[PDB]
Length: 262
Length: 272
Ligand SMILES: COc1ccc(OCc2ccc(COc3c(Cl)cccc3Cl)cc2)c(Cl)c1
Image (cartoon, each protein chain N blue to C red):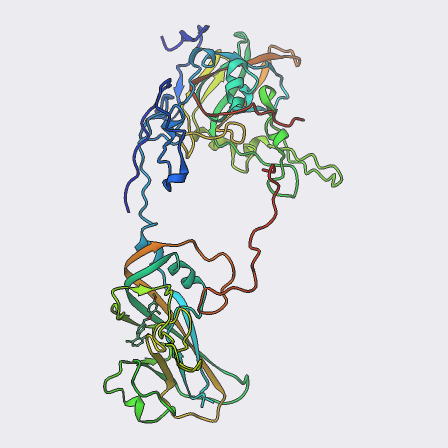
């Protein structure tokens, strides 16, 4: 039925008994580069089962006060097994994804989470200096980031944070959040479903790019209807994020990249 | 101006054929492609060399002269036709030894009052007369030579779109020579040193003649100056014998050099 599914990729399987169908972004399933759209001339590496499998990133907790969370792809998976290895050993890389967000509660809980997949999800910074966010802050990895309820300008001139300041109702980029529904999405309304499943093809203005310099997709999760339970002002339910890269192919092998951190 | 070949997929090799090894002493360049030294994938090539054709490389109007006339002998000026008065077009032409093409000349004319608060003049008309080598050159801005009964003239009205005319291949040889390793005279044994001496690399003393420019209106005591910028574009181009481009500053009409003889910067041998 629309509600029961099983996803198998490599050596990993995911089962769900409360789905609300699955979304295939823009109606496009991920695919490899065709010869007619090929650019780099060298033989690509395609790890296949070693990289195209389900990786579970860290679990976040939803509370009445949560504003939202965000992650960047392939960034969030840079340290994930052999996918991360191939990402750092190659100059160029390409991949699609199957994003599976998990969140179960009970029949006496309420709340709705909007799960959006955004191509080129550029976020707003914290200073008066334009495009000032530094690489280390823009790429948090598997832990991702969070949305805020208001904009707060960083004034420390001696030691600028050079970080993002994504305000939730402004979708972290100066647009109204209610219009974010034009992007592939699903809603995890506690009275209806457990999860959200989105299949994302590779989207870019090029056939292949640098995975370290460029993040193709952004995953934004916003509480559309806040978490509430029985009478417990105190309520916490975890949100686990499991993502699997698809049709990975890398070009331009050399020595490994070791990016600067923190 | 066409397509480039596709990249064919290439796998591993273990053979007695070694395209990587060669011997440049022969004077030939090794025609290798990526698949000769690495494993390649099949790529359908869609890039073309449409913009690097000899025609597209020269298909631009380049400035070759700025003729100036002061409508208050300066009432008229004469410019000896050449492409060596400027450096940009000259350097591009000199990638080749010989050339053959037609020419398109566009004239951009500007004028202005020298005085911010003095004088006035009615709209000016200019006459650009071509004086082929041999024809009488004007001595005054208004002598008989300006009747142009045979010389081609162009009358330009100030403010009108730039004037433009086409000239056929006018060389007396089968192609224009960008380089001429010789003289116009051979000094003979016995003659005075003053005799038989000529410039090295020069052909005719007057190759293509010159342009005589003047303002046709009667000059008013007002101080005015006009400038005619000449733009030339080679069209229907054919070129022969490539040469390395000019690396140091030009020093005259010849290949002479003097000043910027150290064009390259310093860089460590093992510095990326
Ligand atoms: C190798 O590169 C070359 C070769 C020959 C060249 O000049 C030959 C040449 C001969 C006659 C005329 C005369 O053209 C004109 C006429 Cl009819 C009427 C009005 C104005 C002009 Cl302008 C103009 C140029 C140049 Cl500029 C570059």
